């Protein structure tokens, strides 16, 4: 399983990520937390993103 | 695990939220209730939103 | 479970609803019936709507 | 399950239906066959439609 | 029960098909292979199409 | 199944692929890794792509 270690790295390293949604919208922030269905992306406020609506998670720099 | 405590906080605190749909539409209101598949968003009327159609849930202020 | 009591109320009360689809289209009618996957929306004819394509169900008045 | 008796009627009665897709596209023809995942819509040729891509099935007249 | 015989025919007969995606995009080629999640569509190269992203499979002539 | 051998080939051969997303976006890079839900596409950085958001995987040359 790749998803947990990948999201976990981005979390620990408080890396600025771009979460791209299935509709094309680009969300940005740091990954605050995550579970099986959602990812909490912190920014001005924490927003709960559903994984099912995420197409791709792009770190802003190598990890 | 994240989703339930997160939606639960927004509920108790009767916090104005913006639910963004996969189609880009922004719904607004307070979270009245929720289960495994839907979230009741109260406004002028209660509307049943399917989670599968939700991309992101954004509280209008920190919690 | 919120979905079943919610759709059930709209049914019994023969309330005019607007079913919004993931593509943005707004369907209208009364909820004739429903099961795990589809909702029968009566109008001129009964049309079978797949829940997976529904974003939000909006009653035309409080219930 | 409402889906099977509903599609079955449309089949037996060889009723002209409009299948609306999640992308907004309107397909037309008669329902030739169907199973748990797909519907064969006959027209000039039989096309296999995935139910997951169908938003709504609209008969061209009451049944 | 319909999907396998249908794709199997298109395969054996090496029939030019149009695979329409949920996003509207039209793919073309012959069905090289398929299992239960994805379809190999041969063209200039073989491309793996996810069935979940396919709305409709349209043969270019009757079968 | 064919997904695993197909992605595995593209991996071993470090073949430039185009992953097309359900939103129309074309991702490019080499397949670094993959599991049941996601594909790590290496580029400038590794990005985690959800398979559910992938429509088609197109190698840049035959394999």
Image (cartoon, coloured by chain):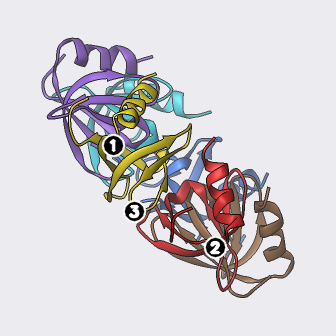
Chain colours: A purple, B yellow, C red, D brown, E blue, F cyan
Look at the image and tell me in which quarter the N terminus of chain C lies: top right
Q: Nearer the viewer, mark 1 or mark 2?
A: 2
Circle number at residue C30 = 2
Q: Is residue A53 above or below residue F13?
A: below
Label 1 with label 3: CB-CB less than 8 Å: no
Query: Real-space Cα distance between discs 3 and 2?
Result: 19 Å
Q: Nearer the viewer, mark 1 or mark 3?
A: 3
Residue with the mark numbered 3: B44
For disc 2, the chain is C
Determine which quarter of the picture holds residue E23.
bottom left
In depth, the one of C60 and E49 nearer the eye is C60
On screen, residue F54 versus residue D45, left or right, reads left
Q: Is residue A35 visible?
A: yes
x 58%, y 53%: residue: E31
Query: Residue E52: where, in percent of width, then height?
Result: 54, 48
Q: Residues within 10 Å of mark 3 (few under 14, many from 20)?
A: few
x 55%, y 76%: residue: C28
Q: Nearer the viewer, mark 3 or mark 2?
A: 3
Residue with the mark numbered 1: B56
x 62%, y 58%: residue: D50
Query: Real-space Cα distance between discs 1 and 2?
Result: 29 Å
Query: Residue D38: where, in percent of width, then height?
Result: 68, 58
Query: Residue F25: where, in percent of width, then height?
Result: 28, 51
For disc 3, the chain is B
Q: Is residue A29 above or below residue B59?
A: above
Mark before the other along the chain sequence, 1 or 3: 3
On screen, residue E26 versus residue C45, left or right, reads left
Label 1 with label 2: CB-CB less than 8 Å: no
Q: Is residue E40 visible?
A: no
Q: Residues within 10 Å of mark 2 (few under 14, many from 20)?
A: many
């Amino acid at each position: 399983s790749l998803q947990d270690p990948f999201l976990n790295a981005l979390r620990r390293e408080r890396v600025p990520v771009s979460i791209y949604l299935v509709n094309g919208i680009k969300l940005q922030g740091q990954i605050e937390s995550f579970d099986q269905f959602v990812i909490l992306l912190k920014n001005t406020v924490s927003q709960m993103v559903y994984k099912h609506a995420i197409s791709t998670v792009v770190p802003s720099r190598p990890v």
